[PDB]
Image 1 (cartoon, protein in one colour):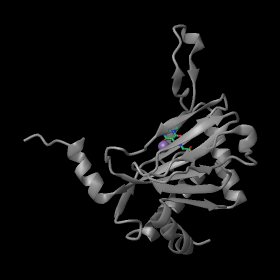
Image 2 (tube, rainbow, N blue to C red):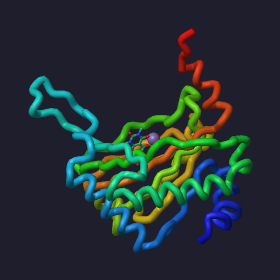
Image 3 (tube, rainbow, N blue to C red):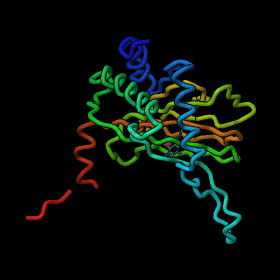
Image 4 (cartoon, rainbow, N blue to C red):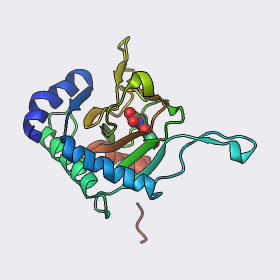
Length: 221
Ligand SMILES: Cn1c(O)c(C(=O)NCC(=O)O)c(=O)n(C)c1=O
Ligand SMILES: [Mn+2]
């Protein structure tokens, strides 16, 4: 669908009502699988980190490591389709501007490409932006074809604030996810027993980001 119809008829109302929004089949099989090929290419050539240190053993060779990451601008060689994903995200947000809460989005981070190795590691419950660092919207794109959470785990579990319930989101291929980055959406990644790829971008509210600068940019006189 065109960025605008999806943004105006589905994403905006869904975010303002629930603070979470799931869009399936965002780019199609062709583009999605190309992005998967680029991400897997980055992983195979060692562009990722060794992984988040989960359990630090007194013996170093026993240290267990979890999610691996790499920051992608989208202009790198062999990342053109990732850059196209980021451009499409940016189009959606552009068409949403002024309608997502009271936020005026004026920037974003680079793309955090994450790979859970499938060694039973996940990601602890957390809030993305708990201290007003300027990020208002989390946007995640998943790449895992034929994912069976009953078999592979890796579910994203969100605990919407005030609501006695949690929302389970499987990291499905060609799935796009939006949710408020602040304390409204604490969330965790449940242990993944299969390789789990995702691409996250965070969008900045102009006012919050502007006053985060003093919350921490100097000029010699
Ligand atoms: C700061 N940070 C996160 O907030 C992640 C996160 O919330 N992922 C949700 C999901 O993949 O469904 C994450 O995965 N990684 C690697 C990370 O570094
Ligand atoms: Mn998170």
